[PDB]
Structure formats: structure tokens, C-alpha cells
Amino acid sequence: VPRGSHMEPLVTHIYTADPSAHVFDGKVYIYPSHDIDAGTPENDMGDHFDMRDYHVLSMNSIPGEVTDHGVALDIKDIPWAGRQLWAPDAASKDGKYYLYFPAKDKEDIFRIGVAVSDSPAGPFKPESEPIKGSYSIDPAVFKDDDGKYYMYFGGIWGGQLQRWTTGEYAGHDASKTDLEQDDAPAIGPRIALMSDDMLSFAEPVKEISIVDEQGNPILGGDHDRRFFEAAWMHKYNGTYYLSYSTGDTHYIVYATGDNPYGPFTYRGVILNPVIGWTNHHSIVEFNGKWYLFYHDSSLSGGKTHLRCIKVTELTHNADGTIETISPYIE
Ligand SMILES: OC[C@@H]1O[C@H](O)[C@H](O)[C@H]1O
Ligand SMILES: O[C@@H]1[C@@H](O)[C@@H](O)CO[C@H]1O
Ligand code: NA
Ligand code: NA
Image (cartoon, rainbow, N blue to C red; front, side, top):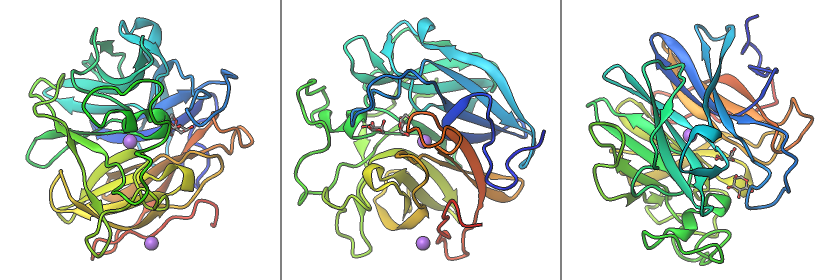
């Protein structure tokens, strides 16, 4: 049946989270996390999120029937992975499709791997090792207008970004949260231009600066605005929009800049807090309308780790500002 009409769950037969939506072959393909009721301990390191595979979803229209293409990748077939298949993303180049995914290696350190297919629906064959120089979580692979592809990535707390300040993992006894200096600039998300073959980074990883309207860095203590996880890039009017989750304050927010590397100036809220702790989204144009894909814990009755994806229309103003969405008003 058709789905996505009135902010209802897009699928109910499985739990789904962290929707990354793309337009490939005139369809919307969605690359979400596949939530399962593992019943593992819930804590601020995210051990309750113990996902083990990915299903690709597609829609020919919004609203529309949602197709579940089955298991596109299973952790049992990823040679380097130990546990926890978290939020993935996809890219298309020269007739090949690339699924990028964060997972903990055998030493319990998050890395980002790639898997390859001839179809946007998968299934995908994983590379035997993760991307060299990758770390932390939540990749968003963005194809710019000029044909260059960039990976945005990172997540603090359980995503371990705060343990990579030196370019090497600081260890399991290092910070469980952030830099632990609230008066210093907050940790920024990461960016790297992708190699021509889409399997590696083409440059040393850069950190993105996010500033307030006065041009001052967003500080570590500013949990309402500072980067937590779920980086996403889209463009409107030639302007670059870095959006992201703030985590413990439960917002999707956005910041704007004039190039992929920033700096980005904080503008405001995309999505107010939902049912359940996490908030994760993507923003995509389809048939000349812009859509915000997101999730909540509504279908499971509020369980943090059993989510469902939803969609709603997103409105840019001509000046580039975006109207804030509150999830449960209409
Ligand atoms: O859903 C698993 C993790 O929680 C957050 O939603 C984050 O963005 C993702 O990697
Ligand atoms: O620290 C984790 C974070 O990595 C994300 O998974 C959301 O849940 C928190 O507990
Ligand atoms: Na994302
Ligand atoms: Na606003």
C-alpha cells in the first residue's frame, strides 16, 4: 500500500532508523539502519544499538509503496568487522553503487568500510578492510555539482570521534564524550575528498569549523548547537548546507557555507526532538520537492533502539533559511 502521506511509519514489518535517502534511476532509495531487539545493555556508549545487517528500501513516489529489497549486506560477510552496523550511506559512480558503513573492527574501534554492487538495491560485496584513514561513524557521501565526491563523517560519545584527535585511536580508556573542555571550540565533523575509484580518501582528513552568526566557534559546552553525529550535506541556491544531530539535546540543526569544507555558520533547527533519544535525518530533492527523512521510536512504544523511519516535506525560503519542522503538530 502507499506510505509517507501523514508522517506515518514508512515500514512496520522491520524496525528502521537513520534514513539516508538518494535519487537513483528516478526512484528514492533509502539506506537505513536495520534495528533489532538485541536486548543488550542500554548506556551512553550505544551498546543497545547492536544491528547486524542492512536492508535497502525504495519508493517510486512520495507517498508511495515502499519496497524492501532484502538483506543487502550482513555483518557475518564483512571480514574486518567485529560488531555493530550503524548508519550507512550510498553513492553512485560510473554504473557502480557503493555502500559506506560504520562498524567496530575486531579491536572494538569504529571504522568506515565500503561495499560494491551493480545495483542501487544491492546486494553489496564488502571490501576486506575498512577505508584507510577512516574512523568513527555516520558517513555521508556527497556528490557535488562538479562531479567530486566527499565523505562527511563522525560521531562523538559512542561514535568515538573524540578519541581520534591525533590521527590514531587514543584507546578504550580515553574520553567517553568529547574533548572535556567546554570553553574550547566543539569537535567538528570530518571531511575527505574520495578517490576516483570510490574506495579510499584522496587527501588527509580535514575537520570542519562551525561558527555562530558572529563568526565565533561553537563551543564544547553549547550542546544545543554543537555537532554530535549524523552529518549530512545538501545544496540549495548554490549554498552548502551542513546538517547534523546534536545528540543529548535531540535536535537536527543546520549551518551554511560556500564550499564543501566550510566554515559553516549555524542558522537554526531543522527538526525538533522526536519520540526516543536519537534523532537522525537526511534531506533530498525528488520531483522538485524537498523531503526530510527522519525517525522516531513511535512504533515500538518509545524503545530507544527500535525505531521507524518517516518522511515529511521540507521548506526552504528563497533567502536560504529553512522552516523548522516539529514532528507531532499537524
Ligand atoms: O543508530 C545508530 C547510531 O545512533 C544514532 O542515530 C547515530 O547517528 C547512528 O550511527
Ligand atoms: O553514545 C551513543 C551514540 O554513539 C549514538 O549511538 C546515540 O546513542 C548514544 O548512547
Ligand atoms: Na547521515
Ligand atoms: Na527556525
